[PDB]
Image 1 (spheres, chains in turn blue, brown):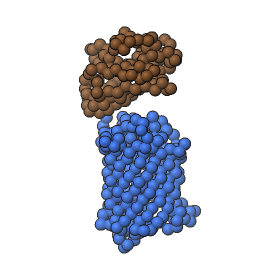
Image 2 (spheres, rainbow over the protein chains, first blue to last red):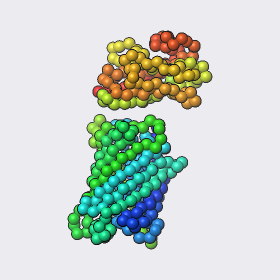
Image 3 (cartoon, helix red, strand yellow):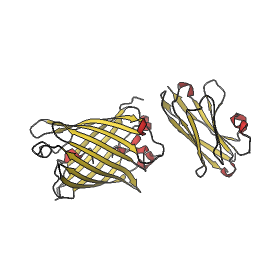
Image 4 (cartoon, rainbow over the protein chains, first blue to last red):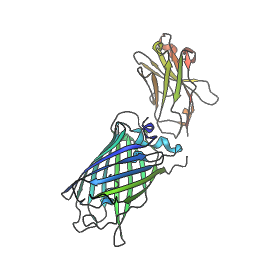
Length: 226
Length: 127
């Protein structure tokens, strides 16, 4: 079973090709995950120059297989059960009073390395809004990620709302709609309803001259008493 | 004696859930001619669940699980799996896997006395 591939530290690679309101950009990331603790450590670089959207708006798009599932909940971990063959993760993200992101990613192992490769298209954004106007604070808050089974697709449906703090003291909500489906045909685990308690912290490498984001994440599954 | 059987997969689920069991056979697996699953509920005898012929993979399902359970096997990996869909509380039991090396006619595969080797079982509970 795929869960056995996550008992230690796993190297990660991320690639993102994006187009938001016609502004094209690419991001690469690398780091490692440790699902025993639920911990991710990643550094991302915009390889095309200046990122045309705020880094926080890309956090959810840029590997929930690294969540820590407590022992009594391990039968509800769809993400690892799809490994190594992987899963497709698709989202629509609605920024309140602004545009939307559409994303499609494949998350899979290539040997020892967990790879997340993504395409993102954004449209309908306001040129002077919080996103294209870079008005988001460089930080992140805690969120609960709600998961339910999708039997007809042999996968899961996921929903949550991200709170992005704005420089003027307001909050910009981002409504996330997500589906995950296995790439392979082997047996997977379909979960009872539960959620992922997710925390993220964003920083900078003072020696990095490129536009970049250092990201640490702690994620633990919860919501099932036993 | 010649063949060791190790079942896995049992756990607590709720009525309507699916659950997949597996059994790994080792030792002198060249001689296997059929494998099967039985189950023993509290206070009941061991009950036939499913059998599979080893070379061709022909399957036999017990009347009370027919249509909801599927048995399959992998000769190269020497495994046999039991896919259990639409589980019910009455499916709660210890599930045992068994193996035969003697040849047979199909009618005998339903009998607990027709198998040469047995595993230790795995507990399935359906609320």
